[PDB]
Image (cartoon, rainbow, N blue to C red):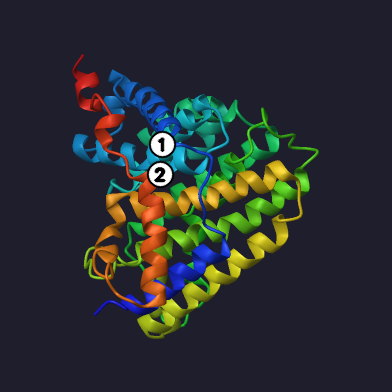
Amino acid sequence: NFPTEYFLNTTVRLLEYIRYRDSNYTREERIENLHYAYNKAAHHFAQPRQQQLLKVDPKRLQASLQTIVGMVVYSWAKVSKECMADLSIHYTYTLVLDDSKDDPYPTMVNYFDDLQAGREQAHPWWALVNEHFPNVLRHFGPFCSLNLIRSTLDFFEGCWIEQYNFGGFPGSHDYPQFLRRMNGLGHCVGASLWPKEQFNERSLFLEITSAIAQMENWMVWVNDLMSFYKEFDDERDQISLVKNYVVSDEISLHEALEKLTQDTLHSSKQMVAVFSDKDPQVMDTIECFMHGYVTWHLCDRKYRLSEIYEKVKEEKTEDAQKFCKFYEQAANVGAVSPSEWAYPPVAQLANV
């Protein structure tokens, strides 16, 4: 059975820590951004070239794009529409790669020589992604760009490793987090929060570098925690961070979850303690990211958190009540019908 009360406490603690609260980011603006980002992305993935090299089921691509646009628009609240759009395309490419089963070995034998010679990469995903990267990179300085480039390369290796469905050898304590950082896009996310149009990479080098180091772990551990419910009974999902802790550290799922919450909460506290008294705009970007990111998890049907809300909807517990109130806040500004922005479907644009 699912740890409903323990889960509730940790989630409410998490939201109190980050100061989860209302923003000046309206529903009308949200919808403007969502539609803008979706429209440009939809037209991108509907081009014949992208349609033929990116082997993905149409319905899944449609669902992945909607999940990603939502994540971007809701978390990168301070960037321009163009920026949210271009990042939506990139993060949609990354999410889509988890659909491939194909062994990367054959397509990576000449990776370096082709890269050094400027020849198109054999692996189709790299062909599309590297060709489109400039559209994402033009929004950033060299330092941030380098971070985006590295994290995406790491991500490619992460997916490669996951094709093995390996949680690590019992006793291999360093494996779980090593893998989570590989597939996390922590430095991609962290650095993409600072467009050169709103921030000076050099004047803020220290705080930006610090945001990356701290945000990397906050972002992945929070996703792990929020995803813990939808993955609890999913016999298909076999190698999550928590599940790998169980196998690699030889501990109970309960202890693995304890470890996760401890790290998540501590990360939340230090996040605040370090950026409260720092450049205002920076703390603002970080603050809105954390809140949007959480909102997105509570509102996206993928994580099915509404099932938890609908279960403890009438309990008199302080936690359950604190949670429902938070959830209602989220739903208040986040719950948006896909028909208000995500249209027409990519497939239709593809036929045209």
Question: Label 1: how many residues lie within 10 Å, few (<14), some (14-19) or many (20+)?
Answer: some
Percent x, y of residue 271: 64, 60
Percent x, y of residue 116: 58, 31
Name the residue rendered at 70%, 55% in the picture.
Answer: 275
Q: Which residue is mark 1?
A: 27
Q: Which residue is mark 2?
A: 333
Amino acid carrying label 2: it is Val
Name the residue rendered at 54%, 46% in the picture.
Answer: 189
Real-space Cα separation, disc 2 to disc 1, in angstroms: 6 Å
Name the residue rendered at 24%, 69% in the picture.
Answer: 311
User: Looking at the rendering, which quadrant does residue 85 occupy?
Assistant: top left
Considering depth in this image, is 179 or 262 the residue closer to the camera? Answer: 262
Q: Are marks 2 and 1 in contact (CB under 8 Å)?
A: yes
Describe residue 42's horizontal placement relative to residue 186 as left or right: left
Amino acid carrying label 1: it is Arg
Label 2 vs 1, first from the N-terminus: 1
- Quarter of the figure that contains the C terminus: top left
Query: Is 276 situated above or below 339?
Result: below
Regarding residue 261, the answer to whether it shows in the image is yes
- Quarter of the figure that contains the N terminus: bottom left
Name the residue rendered at 42%, 79% in the picture.
Answer: 256
Query: Is 42 situated above or below 64?
Result: above
Percent x, y of residue 346: 25, 26
Instruction: Check disc 2 and report its element: helix, strand or loop.
Output: helix
Percent x, y of residue 139: 60, 28
Regarding residue 167, the answer to whether it shows in the image is no
